[PDB]
Amino acid sequence: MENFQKVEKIGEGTYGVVYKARNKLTGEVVALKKIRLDTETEGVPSTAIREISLLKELNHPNIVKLLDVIHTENKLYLVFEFLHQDLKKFMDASALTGIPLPLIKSYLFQLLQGLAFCHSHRVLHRDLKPQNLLINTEGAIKLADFGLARAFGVPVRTYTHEVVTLWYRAPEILLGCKYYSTAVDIWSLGCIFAEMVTRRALFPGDSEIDQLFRIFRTLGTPDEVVWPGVTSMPDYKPSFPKWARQDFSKVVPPLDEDGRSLLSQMLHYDPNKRISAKAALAHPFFQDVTKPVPHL
Amino acid sequence: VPDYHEDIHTYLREMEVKCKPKVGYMKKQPDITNSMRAILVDWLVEVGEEYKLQNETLHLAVNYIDRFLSSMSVLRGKLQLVGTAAMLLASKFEEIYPPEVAEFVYITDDTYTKKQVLRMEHLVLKVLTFDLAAPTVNQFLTQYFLHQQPANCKVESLAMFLGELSLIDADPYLKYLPSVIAGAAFHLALYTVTGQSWPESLIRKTGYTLESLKPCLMDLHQTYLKAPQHAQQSIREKYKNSKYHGVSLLNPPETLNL
Ligand SMILES: CC[C@H](C)[C@H](NC(=O)[C@H](CC(C)C)NC(=O)[C@H](CCCN=C(N)N)NC(=O)c1nc(C)n(-c2ccc(Cl)cc2)n1)C(=O)N[C@@H](Cc1ccc(F)cc1)C(N)=O
Image (tube, rainbow over all chains, first blue to last red; front, side, top):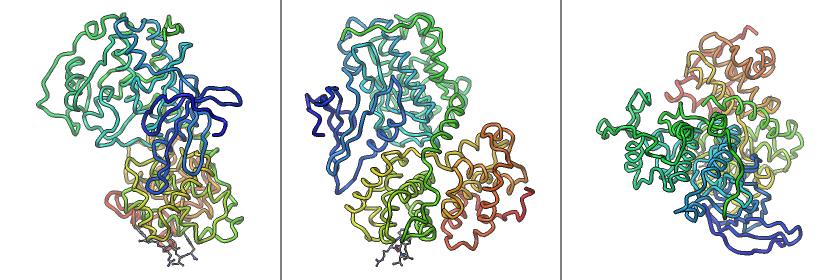
């Protein structure tokens, strides 16, 4: 800790403030996530236990690198590689102009590789939203904030009451499914894809029921043909309005026939048929992908 | 599901070798014994029943205890503190809402303080260098079950049962990787319920032939015969539940055709 000079605060994401800091000896700029130990009521919080244990196994160019954990009596310090900003802020500032298509494809391609790497190491992220996606000035993008991530060596049981974001939540979870699967990550990612493309959140719901109905209204209301099982899901009702599957051309105008095709595969209703991150990397949409750098 | 099954299986095989305890460690412990360790693990099975903890959480806690007692000496009077911190850490990592620290202090019968348990928690984290995502018998059993045809769930319980049994006795079980124990437990349960046998699917997947399982299976088969007698009865009492199809009431086979 003596070696670090706090430069400025860059805020929070689940638990404890985040600072930009420089190593006074090597000169590296790092991001310090600092956690207060309530050493008399809770201990090390479970967000930290998970993010540290999980992120220590994952070493990949599209997953934020955990450099060191500095482990004192009263404080835990997490030291990460520094990254200039998140995609959420970027989309706010690229708003009105849009994010250039080609950077969209680069971003998605890189996210898919990070995801694919998590999922092949039995790690679920579970909380993919743009504020968790960190970009630098060289055009890279990385999965961050593994506070909620879980190992799925055994299947992961769903929180009856989700502290786990609304807009990017999969329909199987909204319909009271009882396990997560890698499909929930793919769903978030597809929403975030349409968000970059159209410039606003695909399904910005206001409760769980509003979420479903916003999804149902765009993708059409599921039945047993599209989604074998739906009608026997704890939170399903025979009374749900029956909407029609809107044309994807209308949902994501700026996108070509291949984008639309991939997008719709990442948003299949049936978790069993939803495209995996491995398979998505093979998609024709990625044929001309390059590595442009943002105007940041 | 099955886009990553095999990557996962392969990678759990790699991790399990990283997360292996030192096998002759109880001998280097001057004040604690395999038998004390059995007392502690059985007590953990009960704490887990009581708070409705997942079974995974128990296997995790057992792995932490054994990697810990592997590099740190503990006097008998602190063994349980190491166990309680272990259970707390396993809960935070695996459970949705972990029981609070007060609760863990509470179930030792205020035998340590809330701050002792937290200082122990920190010290376990340091010794395990935060490596908590450990592969368990329960993990491999869960992977194995995808390969059974048709699914028998008396088979599953009975396998889980045998796999929990093996946690109690470092006596033979620290010699086997979790993937090997899960293997013999699966075969033994399949066998006992139906007379079938460690399937070809899983020979090709695990590269474990029935023959390679034979040493572990023999110990396991001994454990299963002697279960009703063992000093520790917690796992049996647990596995009497209708939730488990009272598999621990079922009759062990006396021979194995091995
Ligand atoms: C009371 C003294 C005896 C001799 C001692 N027993 C214990 O240490 C056991 C160990 C646990 C893991 C079963 N601990 C307890 O009984 C302690 C009492 C503390 C000792 N009493 C004093 N100092 N007056 N209490 C409990 O563990 C306890 N209390 C409750 C309630 N529960 C409980 C149990 C189940 C549930 Cl679901 C909920 C709560 N457990 C013991 O048997 N020690 C062993 C050594 C040993 C130490 C730890 C260990 F895990 C195994 C052996 C020996 N010397 O042979």
